[PDB]
Image 1 (cartoon, rainbow, N blue to C red):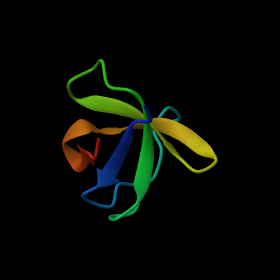
Image 2 (cartoon, helix red, strand yellow):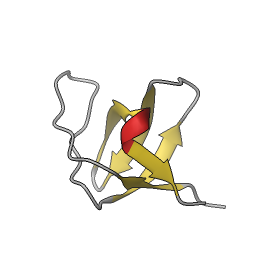
Image 3 (spheres, helix red, strand yellow):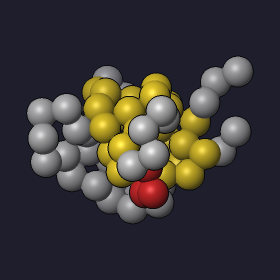
Image 4 (cartoon, rainbow, N blue to C red):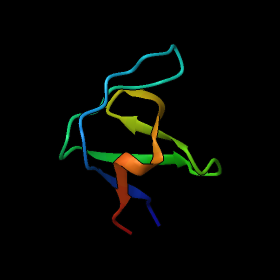
Length: 58
């Protein structure tokens, strides 16, 4: 019942509520209620990244 997404691109956080990811990272999806920005967990950090830059795996 987990929810994982694949990072399709690098993304560097540009705001306090964003988080950085590297292409190929496997992120835990926390909140996908917004169509443009998804909240994800990238290890010990959480924050928003662009929804289009990740892909649901499950």
